Image 1 (spheres, rainbow, N blue to C red):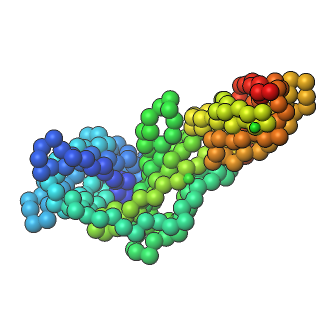
Image 2 (tube, rainbow, N blue to C red):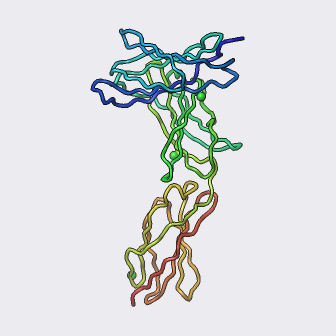
Image 3 (cartoon, rainbow, N blue to C red):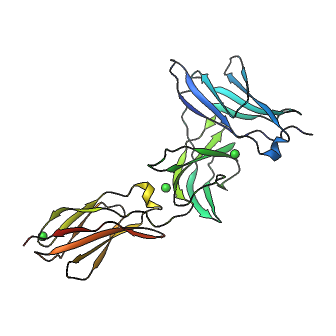
Length: 290
Ligand SMILES: [Cl-]
Ligand SMILES: [Cl-]
Ligand SMILES: [Cl-]
C-alpha cells in the first residue's frame, strides 16, 4: 500500500497569552479525505521552529493542538502518518507579533449556483501559496462559529465545501497565504438562497401634524431578513379611504408622510422586501390634529 498522498489542510488562530511575552496559538487541520489517507491514520506530527532556536516536536492524535509561542517568527510543519509512512508536510510561517498583513484579494464576490455557494476574487499581485476560506452564519440566535477550507494558490473561484442552509446570511472571509505569513483578509456576506422576510418592520409615529406624520422604525434583526433588504413599502389609508403605497430606501429608518388630511384617523403598515418577496409588519394607527 501507500502513505498519505497529500499534506492536510493546515491553519491557525492566534491570541494573547495569560503569560507575558507569549501568544496562545491554536493550530488546526482537517482529517484527510479517505482517498488521500490511504489507510488508517495513526497520528500527526507538528514541528515548530523559532528563528535561530531549537525545534519543538509534538505527536498528536486529534485535529488541533494548542501551543504557546513567543513573539518571534516560527516555521510550523504538519505531517500525517499511516502504517506505510508520512505525508508530505503542510508548512506555514507564523509571523512575529509586529507583522503587518497586506495584499488582500480584490473584487471579492459570492453567489449561489446549482445549489452551491460560490466565492470568487481577482488574484493578488503577489505569489499566493494557498488560500484559507472561512464562513459562519450571522444570527442573533446563534454565535458565529466558523468552518473553513483551504485552496491551492492558483485558485480564483471555488464553492464552500460545507453543507449549508437556505435563508441564512453567511459571512465569508478569504485570506491569501504567502511565504512570510498571511495576507490581509477580506469578507463578504451572501445567501445560498434568499426568501421573503419572516417579519416586517414595526412602525411608530415620531411626530404628527395636521397634514404630515413622521414615521420611524427599527431595522429588522438579521435573523428575520432571510435575504438582503432591498426596500420598504409604506401602506396607509384613512379609515374610510383607499390605500396609498410609497416606496422607501432600505437604508432609511425615518420617513415623513405628507398631503395628509387633518382631523383624520389613519391606518398604516410597512413591508420589507428581499429579492424573493415581501412581508408586512403590524398595523399602526394615528389621528391627525384638527
Ligand atoms: Cl480543505
Ligand atoms: Cl457583503
Ligand atoms: Cl403638518
